[PDB]
Length: 132
Length: 142
Image (cartoon, rainbow over the protein chains, first blue to last red):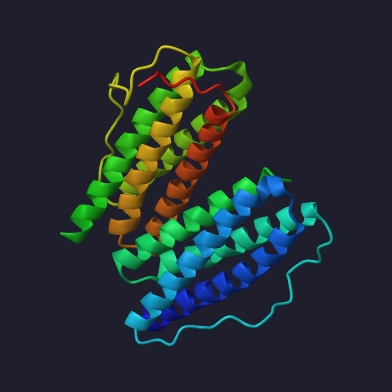
């Protein structure tokens, strides 16, 4: 392995995090009050993880990806039910991104960080999967 | 040594798996019929993971720790509600043991396996916590 593979996977995961946090704005807007705490949970988790990743990249001397002002969603939505499905998809995409950081991270500290993020993503997908 | 810590972590995780499979026998005997889909699921997941780790340790030139006849369970139990708490404690202990394998595993293949095991243990714990949360909470007055 390579520090170049490590950096690319972590930057890819940060780009995913940016997109997911944007996506949770639409999930929030569409979802009923009964899932407000789930949305707030997911947004806080993603924002904190994003911020931490920006710090990890800076320690590496890599300028972190920034968020786009706007994203094309990976599915069309018109429903609270659609919002749950979108949240499931984003958490699953986050898991795939974090699994690649576990594989390519050179240090144990960063591998353990990525494992935590992969595990939170998976747990979050299951929680929204119980919404639909 | 590095491979020394790797082997040690995976042996510990295997030992936790044996102890978990034993504990789910008790979870099952006590439980609700209402959660036997969950118990069956958890047991097949653990038995399969255990067998997988037995193979991995062999690939490394390590003869696997075999199961003990009995274990001391992580907590005392006496009814159907204690068993869901036991299941959460067992899954949480399994996450802890798998996070150690992620941390000390030298190969990407073994770290991916350990992270999958870690994530499954975490998803299992949340599922049992969802079971507890749907049952009456009856905390003793302090």
